[PDB]
Image 1 (cartoon, helix red, strand yellow):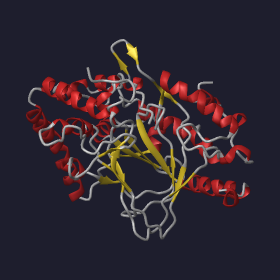
Image 2 (image 1 turned 180 degrees about the horizontal axis):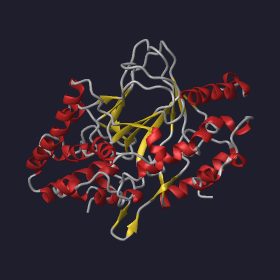
Image 3 (image 1 turned 90 degrees about the horizontal axis):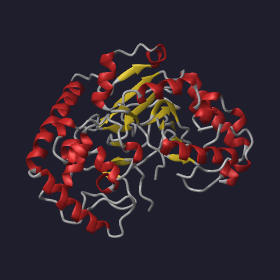
Image 4 (image 1 turned 30 degrees about the vertical axis):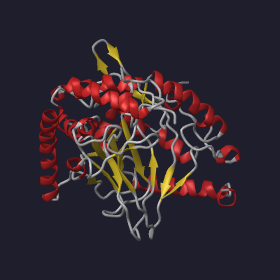
Length: 397
């Protein structure tokens, strides 16, 4: 047919056959697209009404409620409707600020300046690993993972109560920073969204025109997705990060299209009649899937900034959620973040977990990132001996 488990040799030819196949399957894609657009528009309307009232768009939950298990059904519903969430006070402010200073002292101790939106190529600081295997992070990941329908029919697609250690970096942006930011896009695959057999199953109700039956919270088959090698090696239910510093409004902040089903619009857009044969509305090999005003005006107008944050808060967004980082000139305040996602245990993530453990043991850069291995001979590094039981399970040990 047109699907391919790995990068097709001639991606343009594969794209042309996929369009012919799916357009035939859809029958009247334009009509389907208009209805989906109207539905998405109801959400955009809700969002603008909230913004007009100065009301919060991003769902806001207190970590206190997550910890006590007192998040209401209405709150859970809201997160599922918006596809994102802010966890207030996930970690006390002084703990998050302490982590930031701890990592700086770690860098000084190992003379980083002599051996080396500045993204730090460090992964094994005490702060990073302790935050990752903390009871607070575990409670958050479990809660978020459970917003998904992970058990479908007679199969459990993933363990929502155990998330794998996904070693990532930290980003520090001091006052005065001027950055272009990052254009709107989605991760977890680009061309794969259309050509990967697994994604054809995930988005079956999108490509067959039964949008009413498409549920972005249905986990089935997402765990079978393997991004092309031209990259993320794990299945994430939510991307996310913890604020290491307070973050002020308008200062080049994270924005998202708080509509998880927006991906359906993205998937059908290239199938309309104003799209060149070979083109996929900006999608290109080895690049993140872009979302623009040119191809997705309805979606771009829904981009919504995170609200003001205090160090210790954490923000999360569904794996299909479109996000960006607005540009900033002469940034006020700091913009420090520690990236920590939610990747529930499953065959795919267990395979990466074994690799993570080996990298940790050596203090080397994780496979998904550039091979810099700065920490291989650093002192004060988090080691296997520092792992608590939760950390061990998160590493498939």
